[PDB]
Image (cartoon, rainbow, N blue to C red):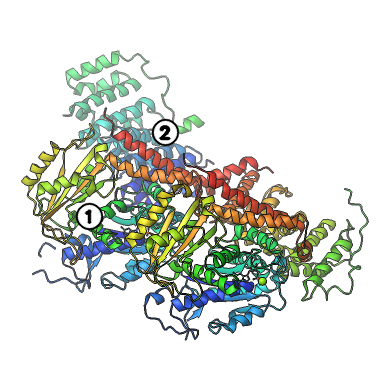
Amino acid sequence: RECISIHVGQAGVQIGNACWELYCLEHGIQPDGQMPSDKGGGDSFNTFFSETGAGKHVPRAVFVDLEPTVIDEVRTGTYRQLFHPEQLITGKEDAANNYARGHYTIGKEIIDLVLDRIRKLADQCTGLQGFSVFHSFGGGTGSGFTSLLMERLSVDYGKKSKLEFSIYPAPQVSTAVVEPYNSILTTHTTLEHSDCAFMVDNEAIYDICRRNLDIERPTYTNLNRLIGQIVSSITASLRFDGALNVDLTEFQTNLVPYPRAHFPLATYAPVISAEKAYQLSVAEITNACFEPANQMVKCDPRHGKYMACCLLYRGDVVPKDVNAAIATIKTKRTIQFVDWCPTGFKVGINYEPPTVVPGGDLAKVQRAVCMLSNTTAIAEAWARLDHKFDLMYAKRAFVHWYVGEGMEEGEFSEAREDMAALEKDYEEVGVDS
Amino acid sequence: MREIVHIQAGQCGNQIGAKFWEVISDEHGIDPTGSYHGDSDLQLERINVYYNEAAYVPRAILVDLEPGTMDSVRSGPFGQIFRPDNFVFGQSGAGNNWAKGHYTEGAELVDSVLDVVRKESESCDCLQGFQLTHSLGGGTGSGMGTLLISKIREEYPDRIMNTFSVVPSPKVSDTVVEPYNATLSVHQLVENTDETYCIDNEALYDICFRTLKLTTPTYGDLNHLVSATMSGVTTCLRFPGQLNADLRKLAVNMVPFPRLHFFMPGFAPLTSRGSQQYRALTVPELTQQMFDAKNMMAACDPRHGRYLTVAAVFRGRMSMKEVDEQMLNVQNKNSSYFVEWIPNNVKTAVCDIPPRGLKMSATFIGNSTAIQELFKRISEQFTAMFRRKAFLHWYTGEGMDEMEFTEAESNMNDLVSEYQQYQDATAD
Amino acid sequence: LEQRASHKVWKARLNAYQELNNLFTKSSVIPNDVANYWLDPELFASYIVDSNVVAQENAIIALHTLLEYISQVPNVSTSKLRLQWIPPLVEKGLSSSRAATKAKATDCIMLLTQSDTSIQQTVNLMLPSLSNKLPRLVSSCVKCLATIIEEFGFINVSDINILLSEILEPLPKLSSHADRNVRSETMNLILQIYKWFGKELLQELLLEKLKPIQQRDLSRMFEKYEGTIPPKQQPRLFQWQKEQPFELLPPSVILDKFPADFQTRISSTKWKDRVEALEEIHNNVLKPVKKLAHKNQDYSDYLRVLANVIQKDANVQAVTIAANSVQLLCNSLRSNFTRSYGAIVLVPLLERTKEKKPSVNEAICSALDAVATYCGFDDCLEETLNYMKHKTPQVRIECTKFLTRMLQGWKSDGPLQNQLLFKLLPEVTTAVLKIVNDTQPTTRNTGFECFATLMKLVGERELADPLEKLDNLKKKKIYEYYEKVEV
Ligand SMILES: Nc1nc2c(ncn2[C@@H]2O[C@H](COP(=O)(O)OP(=O)(O)OP(=O)(O)O)[C@@H](O)[C@H]2O)c(=O)[nH]1
Ligand SMILES: Nc1nc2c(ncn2[C@@H]2O[C@H](COP(=O)(O)OP(=O)(O)O)[C@@H](O)[C@H]2O)c(=O)[nH]1
Ligand SMILES: [Mg+2]
Ligand SMILES: [Mg+2]
């Protein structure tokens, strides 16, 4: 049942704000944690909220940062009463975009305190399902401390699953040069601890906001609200009940053919700005899932082979309209499956409309769909990181910072060897027999 | 990573340090009495970095062996705001001798400074780093400064050490032992400081003479460019920004190799003292004047080297989108002067608040391999005197062995060779 | 994790069973008190009945290697084991449907039987199992029963007639069982009884009560047996069966040469006075000698004024020339720094290792080496470890290097149990690990050597325990120095 969300670093914390704000809007929860009386009523959403005896609904979330600045805004803004202050953990000295600081030097000072506050939430749960980790790839805390927390969760909560929403870096909003270093280092130490990893290329969200919302330079709020829409569609299976609302844990069984190939590609549609008049059918929003301009990780699935394809519909969506659209796309596009896969599409439907932030930049839509596809083309993202990594590491540039914070230089080599094998593993999977 | 402890040492250190505190106290709306008389709240958002709470007092320590500049600062306009106990001034001078400040009479006073350093550090919620202003060609700021750095290094090995070191030149001061002091001081900064802004006086002079068209530049004419440059390179630290917020994040983005932490600062537009330059330059202008040699505070031609890392800081209300187009343009149009094997090495930040007197300004911070020209220049003057062992009895009479000069000369030439080494490395 | 052998989650239980299987194969044979699984046999009697068939299989293979481990004198406590263990082995090991889980349970029953003195105190426990509902259980443990007779046989059993009649009682019922396998395995058990006795006996007692088609089969089975009427030898034995100098120089006196203008000058606000006062007695009094007076000379008054300027004088020049005098003293005064002389300068030298100028670090270290060659580990060992845990990174790398120096020239007096061994892991290896896991690279590089210099003295397997807590990377940098380091 229950799910504990963990938000590490600025990216994880600031995205959790846009997510839990959207969660409250969808479930009708107010910033003070109060809801109207049921007047039963189908009240599924307790997998993400607990109940105080006084009728207060508190998120099962932990916000962690090595710097108080970001989380201080949380315990000051509109949702200061939503979370218990025990769930908002901060340090004083951050990691300075250094994985080794967040994982070895600074992060080890606060790792025991964080696991304690998590055990508090875990002991307030009658049946824990897993963890949802929200972090960046470039920041020192989002890369270093997250991979440290993932190592510790596998030791304590070994049975429970762990899903991560990672923020793939992009130069358009990049705040650090060594972000490729941190990305490779955290992807390596977390690869054997994560069950499913939804990467979010900031360049994709940046361009989708510029193209479909007509925003010149999107702010972090623009990116986060668009991301929160996708995260909501993924978690809606856990937070709502529905006759055709397939659980997310049932999609993972199809999305992950091998433990290392657990990086699905999410594609959300439609994304429309609130400026003119518009209503898209099921076939049009399903067609948009196969346009790479709508993906959240820049890559071309036509240059790769599929292993899974899952359609997470939400809104006014009828099953026969889905199968009609799928049959058209399957015989009018080029979806290459590997020759060892069943080639079938897994469909879930949630008849609640997609909620947007009021007065936001996203328009309320009748229906929407989030496609989760496990394609080999996502290995193009690893190649773009491995290349920027190779350019600097061949000169050992910026390495002294990491080695000066408890990390042995050979850990760079190990992490790159793993990424090299990960690229081979994606190459080998796409071959026929 | 919050509070920054500032230190000024020697004659030039206390000069440009007091002028720097005048500038930022005004930008933060602080009058000499220490009270806040500003309007915006962004001025008080990150005032905790450089100032303390009163009843606002600068977190600055003033050091000099000669008590002359002690009174010249207290008699200044903002001399009443500094803490009285933070003045640590000795009895005798340094005679423009690096060895007197580093080994002899500065070591006899350095323990008094560390007591004030410790005091300001205990009242810090989380000490971010240190900041030093000094002159490499002098005696106290050069000698005692590098000793203070190495002393702070051994007592605060987890804090960033940042310096604003000015470079001697014959066009300003006529003391001949300045190449000795600068060579001995550079030999320390390369192994002790995490980042160092090179402030060439030969560049400052050439700017006041050939650009501002001043026939006889004074130290006030030179220190005006210094205070402006110091205010720009510290903008991201005291105003709520996203990129290069604290000292370490800046050093992590600017220093790819530990010894190559010598920055070539630039600033635009080049204003005069109390002149009239109203029309705020356009964004394409601010970018063109930023990447030229005529606005560099260091006598080096960026055409002669490659930019390892770059940090640009624009101030004033402007089109952030128009900034990206220009900063992208100068990169892909001069791609040969930017290192390929460091992707996205240029980073641009924006701050709404301009410096008092202008509407649009732009500060440049570059880690260019052309900075080797500056060390080549000093190393040439050093050897010319050292081959004749002129004035060596100054330093040997204070304890220094002659071998120390050979080592400092060798390590500087190693630093020059390394800056040339990565200037030739390719991607292939 | 020894108590997780009964943890709720199966995977933790499965891990402990594997950890146990390693202990019983990798432990002592004389045995640890931690191997107290004899005197509480309900522990493994509970593991064999593991509710998880996978971890249950690992609890049995661990019980098997334990059961052969205990084949070491003096464990006559095997009587308590059979009572507590073979009923769980029969009821849920032989009954198990897993061919591997059952194969090892039969192997444990064999070991527990040869731990006994005869087969009777093992037959009586699995005889009730012959009347169980589940035929697969009675199919399996009549085959086991038949194989404990084929190999062990009826020897040294108290009353064989009470045991023969007890095992011949269910045989007519077993040979009419509904299950095809129960019948088939009973016909094999009859052959084993036939092999130890004759044919006359079990025709008098048994064969007449079987189906004629069955006793024809046994006749065919008796013909195919070629061995003698009773086997002339047991195929398997019980445990009790398998048992039964140019330093003759004239000492010069230098405490007289100290001029009156010294204690005043060495305590002056002018650095020149302190530098020149130390330098004159160094160049004119200590330099032109080689053998100082060991008797009737108290240099402790002079040594403490050196430590005062070494520790506290800001003039780094005087610190150099003063530490050199310390080196010259303990050099020219062999076997002099018993306690007071050695300790009056040790900790000021360690504190002053903070100085980074190579000439100064050279002077302070060489004096630290010279005081160590005549006071090996009097205060040094205990005091050096204190300054490896000092807040300054420079004094950490230098004091760590200094231990390596003393550790290299460590010859001791012997034979064993020196001050280094009893502090090896309680304090010394702990202080070295702090350097090995320091945040700075050059600091860790010192500890890597210091650790490798330690493995050079004491056998590398003795320190394999703290080696496994280390990163595989830090293990290669430590093995790196181990090739270069000697003595
Ligand atoms: N979409 C989105 N990305 C963000 C946000 N904040 C930071 N990022 C990305 O995160 C990367 C840097 O990681 P951060 O999360 O900012 O750093 P951190 O986790 O706080 O770790 P340290 O600051 O080094 O202690 C950059 O590439 C940003 O693009 C955000 O609010 N939304
Ligand atoms: N830009 C600038 N340089 C200065 C100033 N005062 C001194 N210098 C330079 O510093 C060098 C002398 O060092 P000085 O500070 O006077 O000696 P100190 O007191 O021992 O640090 C000379 O080469 C001068 O060019 C000043 O006010 N501005
Ligand atoms: Mg942060
Ligand atoms: Mg001067």
Circle 1 is placed at which residue position?
A230
- Which residue corresponds to the image point at 78% horizontal and 58% vertical from the top-left? B389
Q: Which residue is mark 2?
A: C114
Q: Between residues B199 and A373, which one lies in front from this camera angle?
A: B199
Q: How many marks?
A: 2
Q: Where, quadrant-wise, is the N terminus of chain A in this rendering?
A: bottom left
**Quarter of image, ligand 4:** bottom right
Which residue is at 42% across, 84% downward?
A: B37
Q: Is residue C226 above or below residue C303?
A: above
Query: Can residue C336 be seen at all in this image of the molecule?
Result: no
| Distance between the alpha carbons at the discs numbered 1 and 2 | 68 Å
Name the one closer to the observer, A388 or A277. Answer: A277
Q: Is residue A349 left or right of residue A106?
A: left
Q: Estimate how packed mark 2 is, as few (under 14), some (14 to 19) or many (20 or more) residues with alpha carbons within 10 Å.
A: many
Please state which of the two labelled residues, at mark 1 or mark 2, is closer to the viewer. 1
Task: Give x and y (percent) for residue B265.
Answer: 51, 62
Question: Disc 1 vs disc 2: Cβ atoms closer than 8 Å?
Answer: no
Say which quadrant the C terminus of chain A sits in: top left
